[PDB]
Structure formats: C-alpha cells, structure tokens
Length: 605
Length: 30
Ligand SMILES: *[C@@H]1O[C@H](CO)[C@@H](O[C@@H]2O[C@H](CO)[C@@H](O)[C@H](O)[C@H]2NC(C)=O)[C@H](O)[C@H]1NC(C)=O
Ligand SMILES: *[C@@H]1O[C@H](CO)[C@@H](O)[C@H](O)[C@H]1NC(C)=O
Ligand SMILES: *[C@@H]1O[C@H](CO)[C@@H](O)[C@H](O)[C@H]1NC(C)=O
Ligand SMILES: *[C@@H]1O[C@H](CO)[C@@H](O)[C@H](O)[C@H]1NC(C)=O
Ligand SMILES: *[C@@H]1O[C@H](CO)[C@@H](O)[C@H](O)[C@H]1NC(C)=O
Ligand SMILES: CC(C)C[C@H](N)C(=O)O
Image 1 (cartoon, protein in one colour):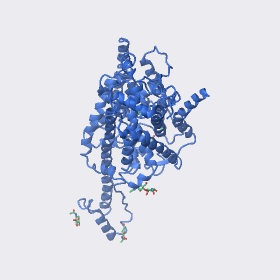
Image 2: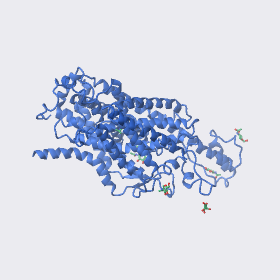
Image 3: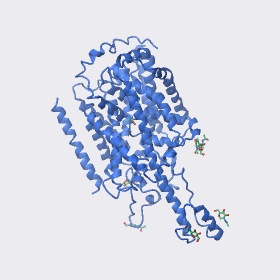
C-alpha cells in the first residue's frame, strides 16, 4: 500500500459528511424515494444480453455447460465488484471521473476509459433497439409479414432465395437488412432503417432530457412492463408441444467443455456485462443517496435478482428452441413417411413413427430396384437442438418463426416486442449517465447552458455516427464491433477498480468508511474476496484473452445467395484493414489508463 | 399504404410533441 501523499484535504473527511449533505439540497440531484433508486439500478443491469448474448454463448460452450462457470465467476467477481462500486460512490460524493481523480491524480484514465466504453457500447446497443422498433411497427396485421414468401415477376412461383431458405430468413436478411455478400462492399443508407434510428434516439432523448427526475417515472413504468410480460410468456412456453426438451438440453452438462480456456473468458466477460460494472453508471447513481444508507443490503439484493433473471429468461428462450426442434423434426420425419408411401403405393394409416424402421427393410426385400432411386432424410434431435443461433438470430429468426404458429399471432408479436423494447430502453438510461456526467466534470461546455442542451448535443452526434449500421454491410459492422468492444474493454477497467481501492486508497482505511455509514465492518467473506481472491480471478481471465486471441482465425458468416449449399453457414476471413478497427475499438480504452498515467508522471519528471 | 408507416407516423408524432412539452415545462419552470 502506497502512503498516497496528500490523500486528505482532497476528499471529505468523515465528519464533514454530515455537514456537506445538508448543503447539497440545491446543487446535486436526489432520489424521490428508495424504490426509485432500486428500480433504476436493476433496470440498468437487465435486458438485451439475457436474450442475445447469453443463449448464443450457452450452446457453444457445452450446450448447458455455460451455467457452471457463469454462476461461480459471478459469485466470485460480480458480488465483490458491485459492492465496491455502491460504497465508493456514496462516500466520495462524486461521479465516475470525480472518484478516481481523488484517489491519486494519475488514475484519471479510469474515468476517461469508463466514458469511452459507455459511448462505444451504447453506439451499437441503440441500433439493436431500432431493429426491435422496426419489428414492432410491422405488427398490427393478421397475415404477419414474415409468414409467407412473395412471388416472382411472373406470378407462378416464390422467389428463388425464399424457396431454398425460410420465409423468416427472407424478412430479416433481404427485406429488413438488405444485406450484401461481404464487409468490403457497402451500399447506400437504406432509408427505412434510418427512420427507425431517428425514432430510437428521439425516444431516448425524451426520457433523459434532464438526467434524474425525468428518468424516474420512466424507470417506474419500464421496470414493471418487462417483468410482467416475461411471466405471461412463461405459462405459454411450457404449454407448447416440444417444450421440456430444450430445457433438458440447457441442463445436460458436457463436462469435457469445462476444461477449455475460451469457456471461462466468455463466462467472465458476461458477468461484467450482465452486471453493468466498469461503466461508471452505478457509481453516479449511488452518489445521490444519503450518507447513512445501507449499501450492503442494496448490493446483495440487486445481485440475486440479476442472477435469478438470467436463468429465468434462459428457460423461456430454450422452451421455444425445443419447440422449433420438434416442429422441424416432425416435418423432416413426415417427409420420410410420405416419400415411402408414394414410391410403393401404400395407404396412409399403416406407416407411422412407431414402425418406420420396420417397413423400410420390407421395401428393399420386395423391390430392390425401385428402392434404389428413393431418398431418405437423416434427421434426429440434438441436430435440431444445436444450430446457428448467432447474434441477432434468436429474437428475429427463432422467436418470430414460433409466434406465427400460435393462435392470435398478432397479439404475441406486439407483447413480445414491446417487452424487448422496454428491456433495451431502461438499460440506455444508465448508459447515458456514463457519458453525460464525466463530460460535465471535464469543463468543456460553458456552465450556464441548461442540462437539456448537452444531452441533446450528445444524442445528435451518436445518431449521426449510427449511419454506419444502416448500410447494406451494416450487420457485419455490428457483430465484430459488438464482440470486441464488449469483451476487451470490460475486463481491464474492472480489474483497475478493484486494485486501486484496496492498494492505493487502502482497504483498512476503507473499512473505517463502511463502519461509519452502515454501522459495522464488512464480514470475513468480503475481506478474502477483496484482497486475495477476486483480484486474482480477474488477473487470470485476462491471460485467457491472449491465449484465445492467438491460435484462432478471424471468421464471420456470409449470406451470399449464389453460394452452392446455400442455407447452411459459410465462414470467410476478415480483410486486413479490420485490425485498424479492432485496434481502435479495443485499444483507445486500455491505452488510455497507462496513457494518462504516463502523461501525469511526465508532467512530474 | 403499408401499415408500418401509419404506426410509425403515430409513434413519431407522439414523441416529437412530447419533447416540446418537456422543453417548455423546463423553461416555464426555471
Ligand atoms: C463436449 O465438448 C467437447 C469439447 O469441445 C467436444 O469435443 C469436440 O468434438 C468436436 C466434434 O466431434 C471435435 O471437432 C473437437 O476437436 C472436440 N474437442 C476436443 C477438445 O477434442 C464434444 O463433442 C462435446 N460432446 C458432445 C456430445 O458433443
Ligand atoms: C417474367 O415476366 C416479365 C414481365 O414483367 C418478363 O419481362 C420476363 O421475361 C418473364 N420471365 C420469363 C422467364 O418468362
Ligand atoms: C436493396 O434494395 C433495393 C431496392 O429496395 C435494391 O435496388 C438493391 O439492389 C438492394 N440491395 C442489394 C444488395 O440487393
Ligand atoms: C397396414 O397394412 C399391413 C399389411 O396389410 C398390416 O400388417 C398393418 O397392420 C397395417 N397397419 C395398420 C392397420 O395400422
Ligand atoms: C436394401 O437396403 C438396405 C440399406 O438401406 C440394405 O441393408 C439391404 O441389404 C438391401 N437389400 C437388398 C436385397 O439389397
Ligand atoms: C448498455 C449496457 C450498459 C447494458 C448492460 N451491459 C446490460 O446488458 O444490462
């Protein structure tokens, strides 16, 4: 522990705290009640990452062998980290940039990296909401637009790439995205996805026009919608035909997969993404409470709703994957029934699923020549329960195909999509606080303009930057970017926050601050994880990133409706200028911490 | 007419008038 020369006379001094809180009734905002603070915090951490990144990662990492690492890493990094953020913001009375600059003026890179990773994550995260709004506008009609193929110029048959693929794939790839065959060629601005973008940003600027006290009632109405629509969706999913078969696929572990490095990196980067750690929004939200506030009750209540939800969503998601894998298996197996009774002319009430293997041997013993030209499809479950459930391929290709087979199918589309919208809007409330607040402590705007001018300003900029995701190649830009700026940037900052509190500030000084606020010292469970355990697990997951960055090939999926063996996946390699993009998106952030440190130490010299 | 342009026109209409209430309230409030 460095003695940190001049730590006092920079922070409040543990008896000024009762005095400074009675004079901040007009400078800094407040919460209305305790329930407005809890619904803002657990609405920032849920949604769009329980549906999009979790089941996409869960199939690859052992089918259902992703729930072990996840849970353990959660309870071992998640808890400790989330608890360290609620307590360092409540005492230091500042945002994200004001906390880490009062714990040595060299660690100002953590406030500038938490601002740059909140701008780049929320750049593409508000594009997924504009795709959700496009699917909500396309409801309110009983023949749903993704339920049938269009016809040719000559009205005789369907379009050639709607006949080979699904009609749900000819609404996402060709009628929504209008996707191209590579990332190296981009088309035009695609005006109908521009309007939606505008819509999204406009709706985001209406609720956060003044920071807190507008985000309040919003959080109210949006922390209920999401929670009650999921429950209405649970008793529908378990009543389906093929359910309780994708649930068993979620819970049969593949224990060989638990000994790979890449299944602990994706589990470790999901905890720092599900919990909104290393963003700086949960420090600014906890900096508005009173000093005598139990910040330990709040950190273990929010964490057991965040852990319970990520399993509660995953058994709703996998109850409709098992329903598509029974609709497809009963249609592939009905193909083998109908192709046998048409080549040998049998009645229909004799060949069924109980004796298909009995009677196909009877057909080659009767006519060995007429049986040779027949074809028999080879299909069985665990081949339909393991498919391409890639990014933006579950809410748009898996759910929207299953909704069109329920009765009252326009009703289950609206509900579902509004639910997704809510889940994704309430997480952009706190993500706007990670950009507005440290840009307001930097003194770059003249401090007589209102708060509603800076906010609007930011919005415009981000909307004008969101034009790169509306091109023809705009889905290939969102994947790459997504993954990279969502994996690297989290881990580094998360580790810098745990180190600088217990080894630069001081964990023994920090225990005097907890005893003043909540009434007692932290337990022995909080002492081992802060000093020994969790700094280490993080320091580890950080070496697993370079083990799997090397010894892998950068590939991405390509649609290409001229490629032979069309509807299966085709993976080609990235161009050589993608390292410049990757570099920027996952460098700027990290090079920022050491960057500023160096800068200041130099100013020293 | 494309039912998606009507629902967009109602939703973008109730948003763009909701910002000119929340801007004039702020002013007629400070
Ligand atoms: C359980 O996970 C292991 C680890 O990935 C799987 O083993 C892989 O199987 C594929 C296809 O057979 C091979 O290409 C890989 O080389 C295997 N991995 C290793 C490390 O050898 C295994 O298939 C999974 N279990 C099941 C039932 O699929
Ligand atoms: C299909 O119909 C169009 C008329 O719009 C015609 O130009 C085209 O030649 C037709 N295609 C074939 C294969 O007949
Ligand atoms: C996108 O759609 C337009 C018409 O809506 C069409 O002219 C263009 O060729 C499409 N782009 C691709 C790559 O097919
Ligand atoms: C179909 O016909 C065969 C031969 O007549 C018979 O053995 C079989 O039981 C029939 N299947 C039925 C009645 O389901
Ligand atoms: C008929 O085909 C099966 C394989 O489908 C084969 O095992 C069997 O020997 C064949 N019978 C004759 C008489 O060729
Ligand atoms: C925009 C992000 C801060 C949202 C957060 N990662 C979540 O999925 O809850």
